[PDB]
Image 1 (cartoon, each protein chain N blue to C red):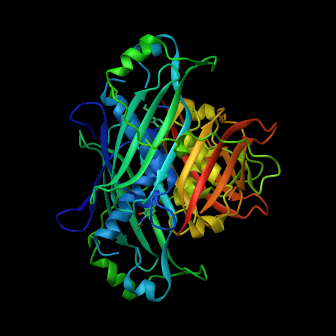
Image 2: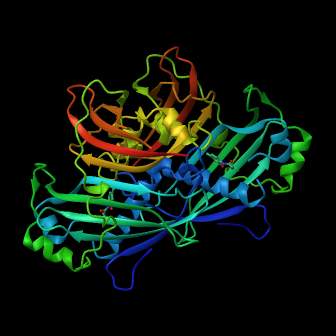
Image 3: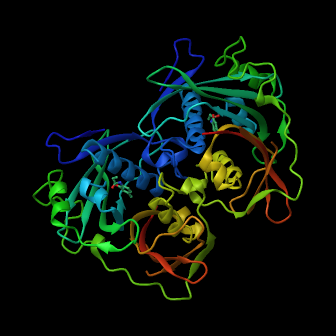
Length: 264
Length: 263
Ligand SMILES: CCC(=O)Nc1ccc(C)cc1O
Ligand SMILES: CCC(=O)Nc1ccc(C)cc1O
């Protein structure tokens, strides 16, 4: 992988692996999300990091608030996918990381993603606005003119997501993370939540449809010793679902999301 | 990746990814097992496949009976690991696939693995001996002289594993596979079983020790809708005896052993 000529974005190629594919011999949405994370980590490393010098001094971290992914074509096993990623400040609200996925052979856009990140104190878990000193430290690595993966006016990445009301149409109960679901800091990987959301989609939908869009809001973190319930209700040739992840015990919300599926 | 000069083995390099590492910033044993599986699949593809023409005609498949992995150094995040793999017939019993793992920069061996595979009818699930016709079409892709990743006479890869007796010292119950745990044929990936075995090792062992050796026997397959209990007892470096069994009737799915070195 490498930073592009202007040093304001990063590109990387990936060959899709045998264990990374689903029933259609194409990459799962969790494989795609892991590749978005890997290209994001390589970009931060290439520019000197995603904690800045000031962030480490104040025990501050970047946490995901929202993830939005749209896939037009899933790469097949053995195919090369090229991913370009960049960041932008969104004032004092936080930062945004965007991605464009392309078929390396044709150069055609096969997917796009956008994510909203907020600043949080590592210890107290209290969110806070971005300070000017932090904003200046990462503006030298971001394009100054706006560059959006989802530029459209009424695009799906910025829509408000409602809370699923009981009873759910579908559910998958008692979901627990294992050690493979943890990152290097022993926190549950953000991609695991995408998997848990999808666990409550009925197998007949998975067998006859392909996932086109997934929007996920992150409200609270699941601990290593927490248990999760995944809930889904159809809200609709295309099928749409409303999703909710909540702790199995008290029903505390972990995530809420929406998925859009098109018939194969 | 590519077949070596003689066409009798296959090599591939991998850069260790950020999500592939554990708390020590080094590749997990499940990342290693996934890389062994990927280099195995690429080898089969490069030689024309791991079912042959005769196996497809009779609905025959290769199934894992035993996996044995020994790691001396786990590659760090960003490091390049080179893996060489080859196969060998073991008469009518089945086939063996071996691997050597190296640090790409130093050329030093950082790990090794061996696996025993048996022939099974995909429909009835009945094990069968390897026929002459199948041995013949496999032998042209295997070294004729023996080439062993674990050559030592009476090594850890060929030791008999006993059945854990109740009560277990440690346990992790109610383990269920999700869709990410399935392969392209909707069967539970063999690497998931390694993860489930390790789930019953206490966190204090994981925090103060590194996994050096894991030997795993595969007895039965876990279905998409099955629930598993993972059981561990210390038999001692720290050594453990392991058992995976269905949560309900207690039907055995796997048995294994692990050896851990103090960090
Ligand atoms: C260190 C750079 C960074 O933000 N990494 C990152 C982690 C998770 C996801 C989903 C996307 C990512 O880009
Ligand atoms: C298709 C070639 C093949 O044998 N692949 C394979 C699958 C699983 C494991 C654990 C190792 C492997 O090498």
